[PDB]
Image (cartoon, rainbow, N blue to C red):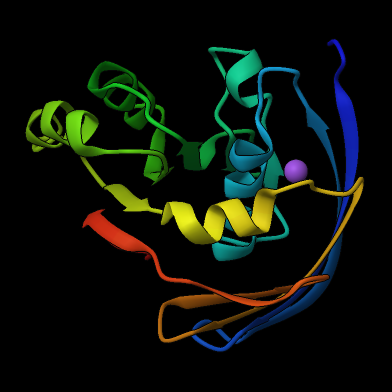
Length: 179
Ligand code: NA
């Protein structure tokens, strides 16, 4: 807030790696500081780590919340997901709050990786993959208010079909794994 734009996400997910087949709808609040690219990375994370208990957090608009999280019925964090370029301090402290920490990084990572990767060696179950900028820009550009994606996940590759065709998202793993 504001302009805090409301988007509706309609996801048909066919995840052949996990045997997950769902049609899901989510409402997402887009903070004015959240770019279309950032939101799109959050949507990819949602599909990539889908669970009925996975929810969008307040992301960049609230320092105490992640971009996405999966909580137990007792409100404890099973999975803490960030997007973008959080620093090693944030990863360290958040990772203590959860059994699994994931980051979908994006943007130019040369300076960031050099600072963060050496500093998180001792962290427990932190997993970091980068989204390539070319496909991200294609996916994110001029995002409509109702986002309809068909997503197929096969051999670790994410194929997103939208209104402009089928786009192949090949994540670069920096540390850890999808799980
Ligand atoms: Na968007």
